[PDB]
Image (cartoon, rainbow, N blue to C red; front, side, top):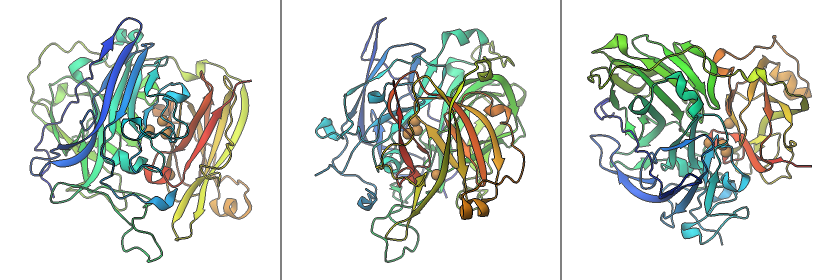
Length: 504
Ligand SMILES: [Cu+2]
Ligand SMILES: [Cu+2]
Ligand SMILES: [Cu+2]
Ligand SMILES: [Cu+2]
């Protein structure tokens, strides 16, 4: 396997506007097939990148900044990863950019059927605009952007179409959180890489049934190798002081459980939807696809040390000490550029619980699915296909409780577009009884969320054999959005549903 910790961690450059005034900011981003070295000992890898970069450029905006991005497809007309056409004259390569966590008008949200081919030559049925509009009228937070094209999301994202997007709220500057050079995004992506440096993505399940098509979708993908910011098991030289890290799980399937091998602590300051009400001291944390942890690590007491960011969560088996048990390495050997004037405050933001909202609707949803003509699992939300008439139709400005029942064998990270939400509780139930009769019989009391989940979330782990309850206010915009599992192999077949936020 590839030698760990021999490449420095890339810090994606911050994207510069094409045009900017007090009234609006304008960016242009072009998807390009490019080559990049993923490790010291590998030949360059063919990848798909925003502005030809993997990851894409980091976009930094202010709260309420009127931002426009023209996302353009200049990719080849044929994919380099295996497409399974059985899961859905249309072009082979379809793309659309979704700003994950964006409080965004529906035609700028990157609807899966709002895709476009090269030069916008062909467009999906929901396509409306070339230039996307992000008003950014939302809390300061770590967002990320990635491809969302119908039935191709697992492939386009794996190809390299991911990037970070940070909203800065000037009202939070007074907290004196680590900033600028000491505010670093970490986009974590697992990959399998061939000897010749080319990306590997499976064209079928291992030793497939002859009934299965070729290529065939797989229900999950676990990469052999871990990358951070487009480099295999990198090192980051750090100064002996406080750093803020924007930790993003940009992987297809893999969930991480992160810790420091010297026994050091993380201080979590934020979740998907922004700053937590109170900072939380953690020795470890779980991070499923699309979840974000905004953390401070204090290296002040660790000068000279090499500290591994370690992973204990298995993917299709136990972690391998020499491979996927490792994420990256910090080396506390960089000379101080300046006095550490940053803070790790306890009091950060308003509790979500301050705002009282009337519960307009309680929505019960089950995670299940079926089997197709080839014998493959088809994962479904409420046993409905993507193309079935819309059923999730919250009214604009109203608050709902969603009760998500998971009788399956694994965790699903459930994501809702547009909104961030509060976690209410999790409660275990009798799976066998539910699958037989449809009746919920609880096997224990409800468990309130841990401090890490007392803030705002947009992607939430729904564990096996539990009912998860969340509360969301559906606004400020009305329109056509989506909700889905963010395991991309599940999302594409077919664990995704439209979500209509309706106006009277
Ligand atoms: Cu996403
Ligand atoms: Cu999203
Ligand atoms: Cu899933
Ligand atoms: Cu989505």
